[PDB]
Image (cartoon, rainbow over all chains, first blue to last red; front, side, top):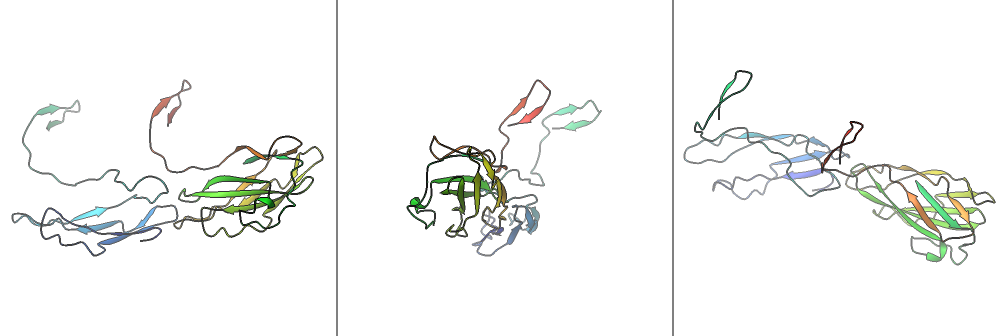
Length: 101
Length: 151
C-alpha cells in the first residue's frame, strides 16, 4: 500500500467457504530499515472438510523484511501439525532413544 | 571516496545554469551509486566546474529521487596548489535522498588525493561506496589461515 505497509489478504482455496478475499485480513508495518515492526501474527481459519473443524492457527510473519533487493518471496514456512502416519521403520540413536520413522 | 583527475586547462565560461543538463556549465559529470537505509540505490551526480586555476566548484544531485531539485548551488569547492594537489575541500557530508521510508543516510564524500594536472581528460580513477545491498549465501570457503568465510 506504501512504504513499510503491506496489506494482507487470506484465502482457503481448498473449500467453497473461502469467498473473495476482498478485506484486509491484516497489515504489516516495517521500520525504515525494512524490519517488520508490527502485524506479527494473525489467527487465521483453515476452512472445513467432512465435519473436520476449521482449526484456525497463528500465522506469524516474524522477522519478515522489506528490502531493496530480491523478488517477493517465501524463505521458510512451517505447518505446525501432521497428517496420518504408518510405521515405516525403527531406529535407535546412540543416546538410547528409540524412535519411529 | 572519489579520486578525481582534472585537466588543469579545462574552464566552464560557456554557461552558468545547471539543472544536471547544462553541459557547458561544467567540465565533469560523475555519478556515484550509494545506498540508503533499505539499500535503495541513489544517484550521486557530481559536477565539476572549473571556476579558475586550482578552484573547482562542486554541485551534487540525487537523480534517483524527485527531492533532488536543480543543483544550482555550490555544494562545495576544491582548492589545489600550484602543483595541482588538492589542498582543500577534502570531504562533504552529502545526502543520499530517500525511498520508501528509507532514511537519507548522508555520507562523507572524500576527494582525497584528487589532482589538477596538465594532461588527461576529466576523469574518475577509483571510487568507493562504503556499504552494501541485500545478500544471499552463495558459497562456503576456507582460507589456509583457518578463516571460514561466506561468499
